[PDB]
Image (cartoon, rainbow over all chains, first blue to last red; front, side, top):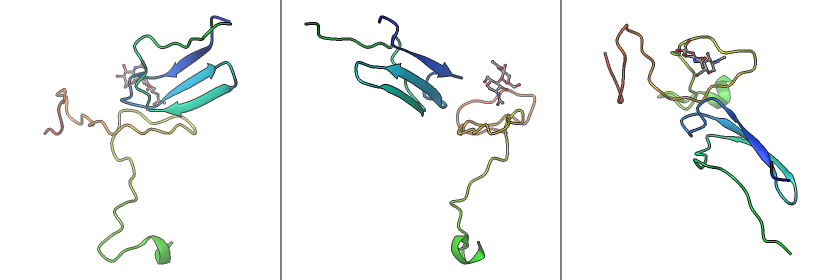
Length: 48
Length: 49
Ligand SMILES: *[C@@H]1O[C@H](CO)[C@@H](O[C@@H]2O[C@H](CO)[C@@H](O)[C@H](O)[C@H]2NC(C)=O)[C@H](O)[C@H]1NC(C)=O
């Protein structure tokens, strides 16, 4: 399950709006904000 | 909406776009506040001629 979502938009840097699509452990979240995305964005887990 | 949305000094809370580069696409929404360049000069900071 290593691929868990995508980011879409114009500037991707909170100057302007952008789209977040994620599938986490629990639900699909889709949201559209002036995100200040993390410069390497990701997710992760505790195992067994 | 005379009754509800008009204030004697002016209800200045209703903003609209007056300056940008190109027209937007159908059902596009633009929330940028960044300065428009009307001259052949590049423009930077907060305000310019
Ligand atoms: C969506 O955004 C892009 C990029 O910001 C816009 O294209 C830019 O338009 C200006 C003015 O023509 C150019 O100076 C840039 O070089 C363009 N860049 C790119 C990547 O296209 C585009 O016009 C926008 N679309 C709408 C409908 O507003």
